[PDB]
Amino acid sequence: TYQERADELVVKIKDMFNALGDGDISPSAYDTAWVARLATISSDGSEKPRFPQALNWVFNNQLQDGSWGIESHFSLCDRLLNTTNSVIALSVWKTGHSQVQQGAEFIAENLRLLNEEDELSPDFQIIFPALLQKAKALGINLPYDLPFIKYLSTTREARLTDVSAAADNIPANMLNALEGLEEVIDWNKIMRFQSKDGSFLSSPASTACVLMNTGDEKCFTFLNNLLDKFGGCVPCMYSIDLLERLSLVDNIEHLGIGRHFKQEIKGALDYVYRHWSERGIGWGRDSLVPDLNTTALGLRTLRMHGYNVSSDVLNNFKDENGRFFSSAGQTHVELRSVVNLFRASDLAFPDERAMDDARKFAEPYLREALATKISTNTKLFKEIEYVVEYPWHMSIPRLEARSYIDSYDDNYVWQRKTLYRMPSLSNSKCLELAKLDFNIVQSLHQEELKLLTRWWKESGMADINFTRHRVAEVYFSSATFEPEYSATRIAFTKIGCLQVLFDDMADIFATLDELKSFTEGVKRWDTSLLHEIPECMQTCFKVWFKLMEEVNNDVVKVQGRDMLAHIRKPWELYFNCYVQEREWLEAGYIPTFEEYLKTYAISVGLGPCTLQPILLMGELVKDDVVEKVHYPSNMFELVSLSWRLTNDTKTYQAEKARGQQASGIACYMKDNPGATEEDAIKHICRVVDRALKEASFEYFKPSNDIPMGCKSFIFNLRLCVQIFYKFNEEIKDYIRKVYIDPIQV
Ligand SMILES: C=C1CC[C@H]2C(C)(C)CCC[C@]2(C)[C@H]1CCN(C)CCOP(=O)(O)OP(=O)(O)O
Ligand SMILES: C=C1CC[C@H]2C(C)(C)CCC[C@]2(C)[C@H]1CCN(C)CCOP(=O)(O)OP(=O)(O)O
Ligand SMILES: [Mg+2]
Ligand SMILES: [Mg+2]
Ligand SMILES: [Mg+2]
């Protein structure tokens, strides 16, 4: 059964968290072969392998086709690098004759397939011809003079002269390709690039090359310890203790299953936070040179989990021209790093210039990549498309999870100088659990919708012709999906349906007098004025009043005491704003921007759909805390502001055509003669953008008295308006994906 399989996967993933160390990463043939080339001198003066275990690994790990590499993941550049270095290692030590022969055959066959249109792997044009030069000196028979191969050698020779002609020798941005630049390196000057663990850019191949030329003891210790840890081989990079923790957390949260791992996540993030630095971070705690990907992932993930981190860490990766780079130790810019840069920018607080710069660079870069470089029919296209089309402030949690389940690749191989696996980060258990859990939670939502449809009938809403499908749309907008908040979602959906009903009532039907009558009835919180309004409005009031009774009875159970006095206020405020709107409309009055917002930021309706539902979540809301989490707290007011203004930009045109003059647009223009509608819309969008960032700041802001679950419900109500009233797919598609179609498991 689903629940049983999910339960054991949760146990298995928790074990993974508990077992986190320096990182789970595959052996690297290219790196292990470089380590295998290293010599030591015996007592008698003869040369022998310094690391015989590494040589033996090479000896024993040739693939069936004669190459070395990752068997199920063939890539031409990877296989050529792995195989050529492996044949070099065996040849140097006069061993593995048969493997050398078959290796040379593979290389010769595949050099004939390397062409000018093949996408070459990072620094391949430097590190590969360096291997060919060595192979040729060892007398290995390969077609070195094929046109494109000669071209690679010539390009490398130009790079060599650039370094030798450089006053300061090898520049930082060539560090990634150190071992391909051996014959021109200044071995004294290069040592300034060494990490505290003795490695060079965490790369065992590069570290072996430095060791070969210098004898440096710290290089030896890094390699010796790494071989011991891996049982006689090495990976392409180590350690990866920061990247692995951050990405495991990020992936789990993104997949929609983070609620199962709260304690494990806190543990992983506490570890990373200890190693967090104003200069950014690299894959591992000992990196001298940090990288954009790990730093951006760090900024986003730590911030998302309430840690205090500064966006200024991003300035470490920005050049004079406002462009970002992945690492000072390389020349190529990695697409994944730019994706994570954009995702980190989603969590900007107000006036964080580094986030502004990050997004201004990353967004065009990603859109350019989607339009020019990425194949439409891939998980990567879908993933990045979602990143830019549904960014954080318009990302509904279940939609985000559902999309990522389809774009998460659980059989992925990473590319740096060569290919490698990180089994914690491309993980079939994580994906399987995400699918099972989504289905289980979905069944819960389906039952909630079943109860809501039953209520739709029994309450009388069906009788008064409330649209059945509107129920599901309000329900979807609740956003806070976790199983423990069923009662809150159900109450929110009932109240939202009445608010939809009320708004239509106030427009299409009610006169001002009838509106005032209805409102006085709300203020009295009784049925004493039902007689003053039309039968249809009476029915509306009665459905609402009955709901209030049922909901308030439930609030007494959860909160431990009567909270009617609190609960009455938002309903009074809401209806009073309705009368104010109508008074202005009949008087043809256009308020100032400030005066407009004072009324319309309330009338948009965040008050009623939040107070009663957040009181059913479970957290204690003390009398003095109501105003700190609900109206008029800053976060609440900011969400309200985003609601009203975003709605205005989307709908003010249609409203004007119906005789409604007051809007954010019209009122700003009245305050500001000379400002066009376009100017007002631009200003309003800036106000909304800032309000969303400010709400984010307020949300993550630590407090000793404000309940975070309640804050989360209010904060995540910002999403529905951003997604529906944004200045492709529609609501029916969202509901299908989230509530109707299960995921094939
Ligand atoms: C795209 C939408 C889904 C989510 C929904 C809520 C957020 C649940 C509140 C009602 C409006 C809406 C925004 C909704 C807009 C629907 N849009 C066609 C609204 C266009 O005008 P309308 O006369 O209101 O259409 P009707 O509502 O179907 O009669
Ligand atoms: C802004 C809203 C999003 C969230 C939504 C739920 C909470 C999901 C259900 C109740 C209605 C509403 C509050 C909803 C109200 C939107 N509106 C119908 C009400 C207010 O907007 P309006 O300018 O007076 O009319 P509109 O332009 O045609 O919409
Ligand atoms: Mg074999
Ligand atoms: Mg209206
Ligand atoms: Mg509107």
Image (cartoon, grey):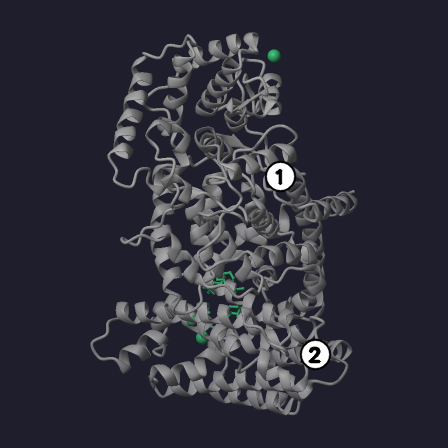
Question: In the image, 477: left or right of 106?
Answer: right
Q: Nearer the viewer, residue 373 or 736?
A: 373
**What residue is pinned by disc 2?**
546
- Local crowd size for mark 2, using a 10 Å CA cut-off: few (<14), some (14–19), many (≥20): few
Q: Mark 1 Cα within 10 Å, few/some/many (few <14, many 20+)? A: many
- Residue depicted at x 51% and y 67%: 718
Residue 463 vs residue 160: left or right? right
Residue at the far left in the pictured view: 674
Q: What type is the residue that disc 1 sits on?
A: Asp
Label 2 secondary element = helix
| Residue ID at (67%, 81%) | 545
Left or right, 69 with respect to 231, comes to left
Whether residue 160 is situated above or below residue 740 in the rendered picture: above
User: Dot 1: what SS?
Assistant: loop
Residue 345 falls in image quadrant: bottom left
Q: What's under tag 2, amino acid-wise? A: Lys
**Residue 711, numbered label:** none
Q: Residue 315's spot in the image, x, y percent?
A: 38, 57
The earlier-in-sequence mark between 2 and 1 is 1
Position of the N terminus, as image quadrant, is top right
Of badges 2 and 1, the one in the foreground is: 1
Q: Quadrant of ligand 5?
A: bottom left
* Residue at numbered disc 1: 24
Q: Which sits in the foreground, 58 or 455?
A: 58
Residue 395 seen by the camera: no
Q: Locate residue 534 relative to residue 548 in the image: left or right.
A: left
From the Cβ of disc 2, is ligand 2 less than 8 Å away? no
Q: Alpha-carbon distance for marks 2 and 1? A: 58 Å
